[PDB]
Length: 129
Ligand SMILES: Cc1cn([C@H]2C[C@H](OP(=O)(O)O)[C@@H](COP(=O)(O)O)O2)c(=O)[nH]c1=O
Ligand SMILES: [Ca+2]
Image 1 (cartoon, helix red, strand yellow):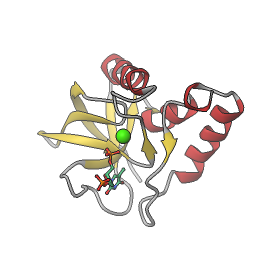
Image 2 (cartoon, helix red, strand yellow; image 1 turned 120 degrees about the vertical axis):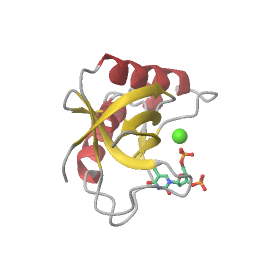
Image 3 (tube, rainbow, N blue to C red; image 1 turned 180 degrees about the vertical axis):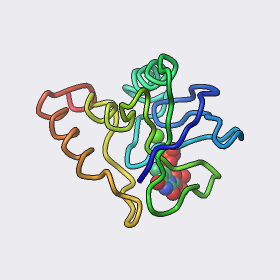
């Protein structure tokens, strides 16, 4: 897998955002995670977390996996990096997302994220509190 450039257009919520990629606006959905919706518990904290991470970043990058690059809603499916730090992993490490939606053929970073989840749980953080 390799990282590609993008720029932030707008934060949306814990696990989706609007990026410019290859010069075109797209909504991206983060691979392998599920944040609560804004109306759900820890939804607002997830949205805030993602928003800060991507708005403060000097450099946003997207990394597609080996499989499907867009979902059925037209959303890009990627791992998202903010100055080299994976947003998807950072959410899971903070107990603000669950590892989820692990489809075969698009799960290169599964074990990395599962390790983060285990530490969040040990710490009883947020969703695991
Ligand atoms: C994360 C991800 C979600 N999806 C689809 C599955 C879910 O379909 P349904 O909408 O039919 O439930 C939906 C979950 O995204 P959200 O958590 O953003 O709602 O997006 C994929 O198809 N591939 C993926 O990698
Ligand atoms: Ca969600």
